[PDB]
Structures are given as structure tokens and as C-alpha cells.
Amino acid sequence: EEFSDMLRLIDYNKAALSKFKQDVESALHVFKTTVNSLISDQLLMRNHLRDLMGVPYCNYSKFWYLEHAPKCWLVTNGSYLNETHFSDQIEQEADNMITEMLR
Amino acid sequence: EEFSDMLRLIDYNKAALSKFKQDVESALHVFKTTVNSLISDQLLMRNHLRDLMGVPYCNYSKFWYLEHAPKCWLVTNGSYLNETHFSDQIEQEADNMITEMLR
Amino acid sequence: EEFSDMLRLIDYNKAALSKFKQDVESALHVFKTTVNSLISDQLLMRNHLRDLMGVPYCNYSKFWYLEHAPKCWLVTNGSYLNETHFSDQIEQEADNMITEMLR
Ligand code: IUM
Ligand SMILES: [Cl-]
């Protein structure tokens, strides 16, 4: 069946996207952990170096800065990256549609 | 219609990819802003620490280094990350094909 | 043919995903190179600043930390990011199925 072959093509596209989303999530977890470690060490350095004491903080808060973005310090204990977890709401709706179709 | 159901499956795959591209773009903007802040603070530190004055710069330019990649300094004011914006050229061509099909 | 039009829609979804995977791989290579340069410079700084000599290393190894994640140093010469290359196993299986279908 040509019908069967087209369903298989759709299934491959769906599976390749799901695997790529998982792979990107895994990669970003490694990047996030690494960048957070650099933030922690940079803060630890700053706290142990008296020659840096006169340097002011920019006091630019996270969200305003993300929308608007030396000098002054930009990195603070508010700079840590949170985990990235991609929504599967669309894929879940597709899965619900398939279960229904399957008669 | 089986026809209608298959169009719906294609539509879900298309929408899930578009949402994931937007989500990745949002995530990379946060990562980029954070890494740029670490570059700025690292440069600010270097400029205020006399014990680092004898350390040379590698003088490896961005593009050659990206293709070829302590020691000497690697990070400079040329290291800042630019914004990432993913092409939708293929999706735009698909949208043009759909508008036409729709008779 | 409606058949021909649906194959074209599947082809656009497949191509848009392949292009996006390539684009993400290109972007992550730039981010990875940049973060590795920040690690190298942070290590170089630490090695030239006597005021940091009493600061201990956390001695948290990469894999346990990635699963479990100042203080002590988190960044070491074991923190460098490796290259990210996304599997195309599913897409390769789809390509093999298409070659076969094509009679
Ligand atoms: O510590 U004396 O410069
Ligand atoms: Cl599809």
C-alpha cells in the first residue's frame, strides 16, 4: 500500500524530530552545567582577589537584561542557568489523535 | 477521510518542528547572553589584575580558530557571541506550496 | 495528484528538520569553542594569581557531577566540551526505505 508507505514516512519524520529534541536536551544539560561551573569559579575568584574590591556591580537584573542587552560586573549568583526541558504538547496531541484514529 | 487524517499528521509534524525551533532560539539567546556576560567580566578582571600583565595574547582570530581549534589569552573583545536566528526558507516554500494547493 | 502533493509536504518536513539539525550543530560548535576558550583563560588566570593558592579543588568528576549537580574550584582541564554531532540513524533508515519504495 502507498497508504502504508506514506504513514511510514510520517512516522520516520516524527521519530527523527523526537530523537533530535532528546539529543538537544542532553547537549544543553552539559553546556548548562559547564557554564554554571564557570560562573561559580568566577564568583569564587572575585571573592578572593582584593585588587577587584573597588569594581562596582552593574545591578542589571536578569529578565530586563535578557530583553535589553568593562565597566561593572554582569555575572552574579542570579546568573546561573536553569535546566532546559522542551514541551511535547503538540506531539502529545498528535499521539492522542493517532490512538483515536486506530479505531 | 484517511486523506484528512494524513494531512493532520503532517500538520502536527510541521507545527512540532516550528515550536521546537522557536524554543531552541529562546534557549540559545539565554545561553548567549550568559556566556557574553562571563566574557565581559573575565576581560574586566584581566584589566584590574597587575599579576596578569606579562601574560601574552594568543592573537588567534575568530574564524581561523573556529575552523582549527595555558599558554596565552584566547578570549578577547572579539569573542562575543552574536544572536542565533534559524532560517525558515524551507518552511516558507512549503507555506507557499500549501496556499497554492488550496486551490 | 493529491498523492504527489502529500509526498511533497512530507519532503518539506524532512528537509526542514535536516537543515535545522545542521544549523544547531553549527551554532553549538561556536558556543563550545567559546566556552572552551573561557575555561582555558580561567585556568590560565588561576595559575598566575598567588592569592588563589589556598583555594581547594572540589574534585567532583565530570560524569557524577553531570548526574548530581563558593567553595572550591569546579572547572578543571577535565571540563572542556567535546564536539556535538547528532545521529542521523532514523533519517538513514527512512532514506533506505525511500530507495526501496522507488521500485
Ligand atoms: O597582593 U600584592 O598585589
Ligand atoms: Cl511529515
Image (cartoon, coloured by chain):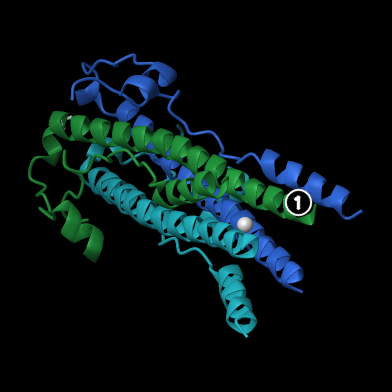
Chain colours: A cyan, B blue, C green
Residue A73 shows in the view:
no
Neighbours of disc 1 within 10 Å: few (<14), some (14-19), many (20+): few
Residue B99 is at least partly visible in this image: yes
* A34 in relation to C27, above or below: below
Residue at image position (69%, 62%) is B11
Depth order, front residue of B46/C67: C67
The amino acid type of the residue labelled 1 equals Asp
> Vertically, is B12 above or below B40?
below
How many callouts does the rendering have? 1
Q: Quadrant of ligand 2?
A: bottom right
- Taking A1 as reference, is C44 left or right? left
Residue A94 as seen in the image, left or right of residue C38: right
- Observer-nearest residue: A36 or C85? C85
Residue B28 is situated, as x and y percent measured from the top left of the image, at 50, 47
Residue found at the very far right of the displayed protein: B103
Residue at x-position 61% and y-position 63%: A1
**Along the line of sight, the residue nearer the viewer: C1 or A38:** C1
Q: Residue at x 74, y 55 (%)?
A: C3
For residue B41, what is the image quadrant? top left
When the figure is inspected, residue B68 is found, relative to residue C2, above or below; the finding is: above
Q: Which residue is mark 1?
A: C5
- Assess mark 1: CB under 8 A from ligand 2? no
- Residue A13 in the image, given as x and y percentages of width and height: 54, 56
* Residue sitting at x 58%, y 48%: C14
Where does the image place residue B69, in percent across and percent down from the top left?
30, 24
What secondary structure is found at the residue carrying circle 1?
A: helix
